[PDB]
RNA sequence: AACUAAUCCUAGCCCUAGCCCUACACAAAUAUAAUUAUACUAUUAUAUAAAUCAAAACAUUUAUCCACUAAAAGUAUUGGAGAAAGAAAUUCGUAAGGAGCUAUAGAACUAGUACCGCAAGGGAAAGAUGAAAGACUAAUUAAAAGUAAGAACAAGCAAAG
């Protein structure tokens, strides 16, 4: 006679049964049943200063939209790194070892914002 | 010049092109040609269909 | 009797008949006399003489055996020196 | 070893075919138990002088069990193989 | 007495007996799940 | 990583962040990414169930073309 | 859904929810499938009625329900009905247009009033244009007001609306830095700690 | 209407590709190879020498013949002894 | 509907698709080329023809292998192809009596064997049949190398086969170190079984183990596109200057 | 002179033929009492299929269940030599459609849903306007049983002469 089709949540079951609704944990439970919040585990919203901002939620109809071109890795490379290498190649001051000079990162370890695996949320 | 028998022009199931028989024979013939390429449930039903027909045609009927 | 066999779909011969009866192509069947090898020491000489003979079958018995045997056992067999050569045909019978 | 034979014959299968079995082809009778059979002997040529069974360089026969446990493994004796006999026969000749 | 009230609901009893973890414990229970997935059932277990 | 569950399917497994290696984690060594032989029969049945469904759809589209050609 | 009939009312209106309840199982309409390239009827194009009540009368397309291969012409194939009927008042009698299938109408030669058949063909610039099968000519796409009703040219800038020039402004600088790294540098946040090793699995 | 061209059996020798797993096995045995030669002769491409048994194959046939099919003299010799025993 | 291929051919297609196909050619041949194991529990027909006593006519005869059950414990021992015979018997050896279940078991023994090539002594569960086979092979090492995969009937034995073959193939100095004379003798004595090193590695491995071995060999972290574009750019610039 | 009702055509389905597959579904969560972001206690199919049923019982036994077409051949063989079972050698072969279904039919299916059982599991029913509903949802029919319109009037298988 139990309803099998309804979702299993903490409102149901005895007192002992509990579970989260998806809220991210922000602290630790120490011995003796004491909660110790950790400030670093609490997200902090980085909010910019909007003074002098010239952009509003809606855009004018008169303004014409452009052609959609999903950005690709090749396109970014040509814009940023290709010109430096091209000029350097003419000057001859280019070597395989110093690709980092143009911005190459050998490993993501040591970066605050690791590209992969991502260590930063949206 | 008898190059092709007319039976070769029939379009139908592989196990009964140019052949005719009663259902029990038809059941066994379907198994022979495509017994190894049949689905599990279809093969199970065919096996049961054969066993039913066998006991009917070989143990029942008005004439002995 | 197996009227329709699974593997081939044909009628099956009963081998109890093949081992007891001989069919002549005309349609007659031959058989032995039951007990011709049994307790011969208490049977009379005339009694034993009858048993040794080969006997024919009736229309019903012949009809039965024809249902229990397949056509292969009803064909013509051209055996050289056959001791049943002359008996496969009926002659001077009006009926 | 246990050597078994079926009670029910298996119809011939052909050349490129396998003899599909049935539940009656799993009834076995005991052909022979090889363990009870009389045992052979083990022929081995000594690599080192053996105790009371000969001197080194002499081919000897042992009762199977004795050779395997000690002579074959402890290095006292070596297998009497073709090459082994050939090599030792050279030492025997050069004496 | 009066029958008909055999079902004495307890969520701890229910989930232990016919739950997801209980079913996966044994292969005989996993084959219960496997058939239910074949049929198309809304709920595979409790 | 592409891995197989105990129900005989290929499932894309998203990894999680852990403070200890996998071989020392006793909750990871309760999850199973393999299938026993008894899932073999069920694997084939899904193939046939999908094959049946796919066959019916193709036949249905064929009829709809016939109706259109009859109409026009 | 398999059982959904497209009618004359714009989908999602009160009329279309009333006509098509979730339990509706009306007989499907059979529509000759027409490729996107094949279709040549567009809103605003003058067409002529091949057959019907108003056969031989030219009209202007004002609606195209491609799901039903329908083209609606203003003031033609028009029957009568009462709009705004109330319990107190009968309402106002109006003449309501009825949908026409494409094969019952034809496009009109831009210069001359005749039902000239057209074919799709490219131009020197490469833009696809309709060309008359006979008396080959370019019939331009007819400019029509947008369904939303917003008029671009007359639109006046207001609060919460960006100026046209401001939107056109481009300031993206291609650089191998994420948004998470550009903001901190611009906003001057400094963090020297680094996350400990994590065993992903 | 004009009828389609009459159905025709494919002419010339036929050699299947052994790679394909659905090709019937009997269509790949050496016996099937000889059939190709007989039907179309040289155009089959079968090495004519291959038709005759190979030396290892030849020993197989010769070994069997001695085992089961004796010589004329042996048959006559045994028959005489049997008559003598019966006599 | 109908499957395009018969069910029994599915295994072959499985080997022919995906990473399975990429496995080395010689290993794939090993799996499919399963040769009936040598008779152990039945006496094979000496001839292909026999004279039936009843009718006295020449009749073809065939050898039908007895089904034997190999418990997984056997994979960790060295049985000479032996296994469990699960069958039925007629009480009192007459078919008119009841049919009774019977299981015939091998008299397993545990002994210690020394491998010259490995120079290590293993303790293994071994039947008297294997002991005779080892004696007829004139050494434990000869027995492992000579016996094919099927006749051996053990996963433990196959690992020994790979270990011995790899030892001979590489001429590893780890065999009897600091005594080169001793090492040379062993290698020469078993020189006949030497095979190429690459082939030796793929000996006795199962499909899963071979699949795991291949996956590890082909595992590689994705190349950064940065480098890939740089290589293309440099080549184009170099060619233009040329 | 009508209530209850009835009429209806396409939703899908069936059997073949061809064809191995490469439909493995953003992001997030789930083996913990599944779908709960992090450590605790770690994780692993199965020894021979049985029986019904047939032998007018039953006890040995009992096709399919459990390796190319046709021929040899239901032959040789096997079998409480009963019911029954049953070869091979050796020959032969280049291989998209509907005298199907049309809503009690065809799949159980509008759905493995509602509902029922603690669970394994079992398992439905039904829809119908027109070109346009941005034309006040059509039609169509003395037509089933059941009623009404219109209770009954000595006497009786209810009718027949
Ligand atoms: Mg044959
Ligand atoms: Mg109850
Ligand atoms: Mg209670
Ligand atoms: Mg029994
Ligand atoms: Mg009975
Ligand atoms: Mg009884
Ligand atoms: Mg139905
Ligand atoms: Mg139903
Ligand atoms: Mg009525
Ligand atoms: Mg009256």
Image (spheres, coloured by chain):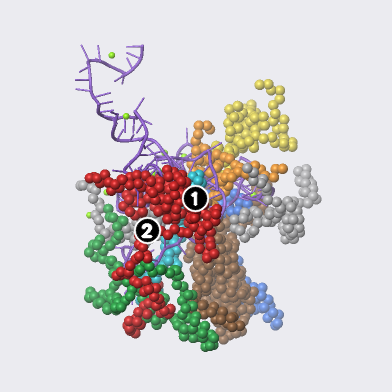
Chain colours: A green, B orange, C yellow, D blue, F cyan, G red, I brown, J purple
- Residue J158, placed above or below residue G139: above
Q: Ligand 8 is found in which quarter of the picture?
A: top left
Q: Tag 1 or tag 2, which sits nearer the N-term?
A: 1
Image quarter where the C terminus of chain D lies is: bottom right
The local secondary structure at tag 2 comes to loop
- Residue at 50% in and 63% down: G127
Q: Which chain contains the residue that carries disc 1? A: G
Query: Could you say which is closer to the camera, residue B1 or residue A29?
Result: B1
Q: CB at mark 1 closer than 8 A to ligand 7? A: no
The local secondary structure at tag 1 comes to loop
Query: In the rendered image, which residue does mark 1 sit on?
Result: G115
Which mark is on residue G147? 2
Q: Is residue A37 visible?
A: yes
Q: Which chain contains the residue that carries disc 2? A: G
> Which quadrant would residue D91 be assigned to in this image?
bottom right
- Residue A65, placed above or below residue G193: above
């Amino acid at each position: 006679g139990a309803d099998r089709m309804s979702k299993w949540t903490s409102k149901r079951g005895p007192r002992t049964f509990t579970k989260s609704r998806g809220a991210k944990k922000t602290g630790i439970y120490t011995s003796d049943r004491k909660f110790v919040q950790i400030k670093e585990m609490v997200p902090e919203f980085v909010v910019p200063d909007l003074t002098g901002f010239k952009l509003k939620p809606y855009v004018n109809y008169r303004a014409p939209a452009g052609i959609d071109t999903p950005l690709t890795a090749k396109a970014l490379f040509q814009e940023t790194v290709a010109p430096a290498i091209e000029k350097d190649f003419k000057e001859g001051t280019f070597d395989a070892n110093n690709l980092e000079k143009y911005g190459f990162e050998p490993t993501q370890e040591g970066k605050l914002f690791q590209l992969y695996p991502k260590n930063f949320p949206r | 010049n008898f190059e092709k028998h007319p039976k070769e022009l029939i379009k139908g199931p592989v196990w009964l092109r140019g052949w005719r028989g009663n259902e029990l024979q038809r059941c066994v013939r379907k198994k022979k040609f495509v017994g190894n390429r049949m689905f599990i449930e279809d093969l199970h039903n065919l096996n049961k269909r054969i066993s039913y027909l066998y006991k009917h045609f070989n143990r029942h009927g008005k004439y002995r | 009797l197996t009227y329709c066999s699974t593997r081939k779909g044909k009628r099956k011969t009963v081998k109890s008949v093949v081992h007891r009866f001989l069919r002549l192509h005309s349609g007659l069947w031959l058989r032995r006399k039951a007990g011709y090898k049994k307790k011969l020491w208490k049977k009379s000489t005339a009694r034993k003489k009858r048993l040794r003979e080969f006997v024919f079958c009736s229309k019903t018995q012949s009809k039965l055996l024809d249902k229990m045997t397949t056509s292969f056992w009803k064909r013509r067999n051209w055996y050289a020196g056959d001791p049943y050569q002359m008996y496969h045909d009926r002659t001077n019978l009006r009926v | 070893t246990v050597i078994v034979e079926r009670w029910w014959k298996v119809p011939l299968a052909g050349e490129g075919r396998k003899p599909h079995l049935h539940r009656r082809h799993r009834v076995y009778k005991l052909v022979e138990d090889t363990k009870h059979r009389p045992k052979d002997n083990l022929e081995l040529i000594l690599t080192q002088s053996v105790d009371e069974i000969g001197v080194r360089g002499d081919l000897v026969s042992v009762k199977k069990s004795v050779g395997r446990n000690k002579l074959l493994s402890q290095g006292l004796a070596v297998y009497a193989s073709p090459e082994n006999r050939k090599l030792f026969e050279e030492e025997k000749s050069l004496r | 007495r009066a029958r008909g009230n055999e079902y004495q609901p307890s969520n701890i009893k229910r989930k232990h007996k016919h739950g997801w973890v209980r079913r996966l414990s044994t292969p005989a229970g996993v084959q219960v799940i496997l058939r239910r997935m074949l049929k198309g059932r809304k709920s595979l277990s409790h | 990583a592409w891995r197989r569950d105990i129900f005989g399917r290929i499932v894309w497994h998203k990894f999680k962040q852990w403070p200890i290696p996998w071989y020392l984690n006793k909750r990871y060594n309760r999850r199973r990414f393999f299938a026993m032989p008894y899932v073999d029969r069920f694997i084939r049945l899904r193939i046939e169930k999908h094959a049946r469904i796919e066959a019916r759809k193709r036949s249905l589209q064929k009829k709809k073309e016939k109706i259109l050609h009859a109409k026009f | 859904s398999p059982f959904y009939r497209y009618g004359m009312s714009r989908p999602g209106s009160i009329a279309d929810k009333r006509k098509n309840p979730p339990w509706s199982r009306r007989r499907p309409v059979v529509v000759e499938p027409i490729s996107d390239e094949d279709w040549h009827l567009f809103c605003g194009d003058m067409v002529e009625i091949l057959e019907g009540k108003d056969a031989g009368k030219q009209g202007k397309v004002v609606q195209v329900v491609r799901q039903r291969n329908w083209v609606v012409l203003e003031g033609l194939n028009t029957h009568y009905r009462y709009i705004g009927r109330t319990k107190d008042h009968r309402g106002t009698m109006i003449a309501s247009e009825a949908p026409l299938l494409h094969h019952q109408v034809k496009l009109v030669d831009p210069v001359d009033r005749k039902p000239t058949e057209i074919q799709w063909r490219f131009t020197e610039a490469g833009e696809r244009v309709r060309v008359s099968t006979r008396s080959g000519r370019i019939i331009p796409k007819p400019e029509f007001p947008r369904a939303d009703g917003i008029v671009p040219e007359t639109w006046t800038d207001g609060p919460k609306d960006t100026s046209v020039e401001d939107a056109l402004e481009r300031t993206y600088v291609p650089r191998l830095k994420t948004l998470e790294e550009d903001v901190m540098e611009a906003m001057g946040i400094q963090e020297t700690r680094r996350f400990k090793k994590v065993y992903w699995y | 209407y004009r009828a389609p061209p009459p159905p025709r059996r494919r002419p010339g020798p036929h050699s299947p590709d052994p790679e394909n797993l659905l090709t019937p096995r009997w269509q790949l045995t050496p016996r099937y190879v000889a059939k190709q030669f007989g039907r179309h002769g040289a155009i089959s491409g079968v090495p004519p020498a291959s038709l005759w048994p190979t030396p290892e194959q030849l020993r197989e046939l010769e070994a069997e013949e001695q085992e089961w099919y004796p010589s004329l003299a042996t048959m006559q010799e045994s028959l005489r002894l049997q008559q003598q025993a019966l006599e | 509907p109908l499957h395009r291929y018969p069910v029994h051919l599915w295994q072959k297609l499985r080997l022919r698709q995906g990473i399975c196909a990429r496995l080395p050619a010689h290993f794939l041949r090993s799996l499919e080329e399963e040769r009936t194991p040598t008779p152990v529990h039945y006496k094979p027909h000496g001839t292909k023809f026999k004279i039936n006593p009843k009718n006295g006519q020449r009749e073809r005869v065939e050898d039908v292998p007895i089904p034997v059950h190999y418990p997984p414990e056997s994979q960790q021992g060295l049985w000479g192809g032996e296994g469990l015979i699960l069958g039925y018997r007629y009480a009192n050896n007459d078919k008119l009596s009841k049919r009774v279940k019977k299981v015939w078991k091998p008299q397993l023994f545990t002994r210690e064997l020394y491998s010259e090539i490995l120079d290590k002594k293993f303790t293994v569960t071994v039947t008297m049949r294997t002991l005779d086979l080892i004696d007829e092979a004139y050494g434990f090492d000869f027995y492992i190398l000579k016996t094919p995969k099927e006749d051996l009937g053990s996963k433990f034995g196959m690992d020994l086969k790979r270990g011995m073959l790899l030892r001979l193939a590489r001429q590893d100095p780890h065999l009897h170190p600091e005594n080169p004379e001793r090492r040379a003798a062993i290698y020469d004595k078993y020189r006949s079984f030497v095979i190429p090193e690459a082939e030796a590695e793929w000996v006795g491995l199962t499909l899963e183990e071979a699949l795991e071995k291949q996956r590890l060999l082909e595992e590689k972290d994705p190349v950064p596109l940065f480098k890939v574009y740089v290589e293309e750019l440099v080549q184009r610039l170099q060619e233009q200057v040329l």
